[PDB]
Amino acid sequence: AINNYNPKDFDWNLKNGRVFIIKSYSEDDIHRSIKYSIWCSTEHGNKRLDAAYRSLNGKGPLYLLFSVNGSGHFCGVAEMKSVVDYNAYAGVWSQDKWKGKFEVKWIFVKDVPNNQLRHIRLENNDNKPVTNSRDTQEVPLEKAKQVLKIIATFKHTTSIFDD
Image (cartoon, rainbow, N blue to C red; front, top):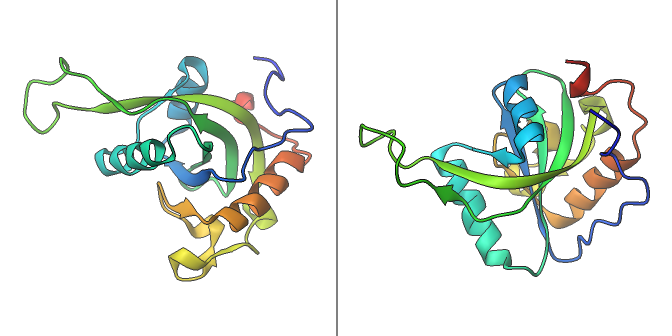
């Protein structure tokens, strides 16, 4: 890998976009996402993000703030880059038939610890800290701006690449 990620004077274009938490079950899913520029949330996760992406059209960016369950930190930020693709061939049984995947462009890959963000609280999630969020929890715009500044400017000592 390279430091192709973590741009410096990164303007977010976050005047009209949306921001969502991703909780990855595994570090492997993070690696594969970075390698192949895709993500799959749960069925409801994909549908929630698909609807948010389509409602935005091209008016604003949809960012995803990633964190592996139990890590204590966020591990980076990607932008969602396609509608959700439900493929029409995978699956034999009816429940594991139409599984969704969508495109992401990874922007920041860096460990930002939660102690840097616990002060930011989500008014749309019972005023809990942004670090308490569950997968596909949406972050209100002004709180998102605060989280993106912290993530973009934090001088990190680790990243998921050490794995």
